[PDB]
Each structure stands twice: as C-alpha cells, then as structure tokens.
Length: 50
Length: 56
Image 1 (cartoon, each protein chain N blue to C red):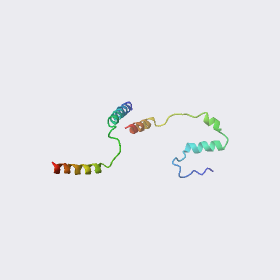
Image 2: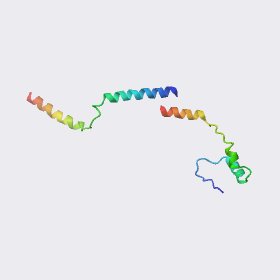
Image 3: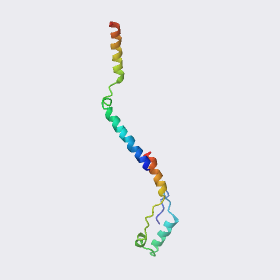
Image 4: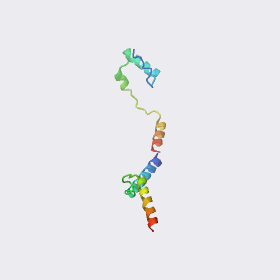
C-alpha cells in the first residue's frame, strides 16, 4: 500500500510539470487539414516561381 | 410475516431468523441486543487488496 501511494504521487507530479510546458500546444483545434492544404499550395507556387 | 423479499441479495441467516423470533416472543428486547453490539471488523485482508487495486 505504502509503495503504491508513493508511485501515484510521483506520476501526478510529472504530469503537472509536462502540462505546463505544453501550454501553447493545448489551444484551438483549427482543422490541421486545412493548414496543410494551404501550405501545399504555397510551396507549390514558390517552387514554380523560383 | 415479513415476507423475505426473494430479490434481496442478502438472504437472512439462521441467526437473524432466530433473533427475530426471540424479539417477537418478548423474551429479548432490542435494547438488550443493542447493548451487546460488537463492532468487530469482518474480512480485513480482502478490503486492503481492494484498495491497492484501485490505486494501481
């Protein structure tokens, strides 16, 4: 029992520390798929213009 | 005749039925039974294992 409780306290602390480091990653789910499409067009144009 | 609800998960023990009978006959008073109440914990080792499983 005493070993299990100590393991929970350690993992909980590690999670709290990682969530704080990842504050910028947690914002609004803009449709990742749309950004990639747009990027695809821009790159393709860039290549053609070069 | 407190018709044992057949669907109660806990079936009445012979001890319980005997105690009930003794109380109905006025030979035993509920006060006498209350004063005799043993809070002795039953199955302590099984309870500890349940707590460990939850934490895990």
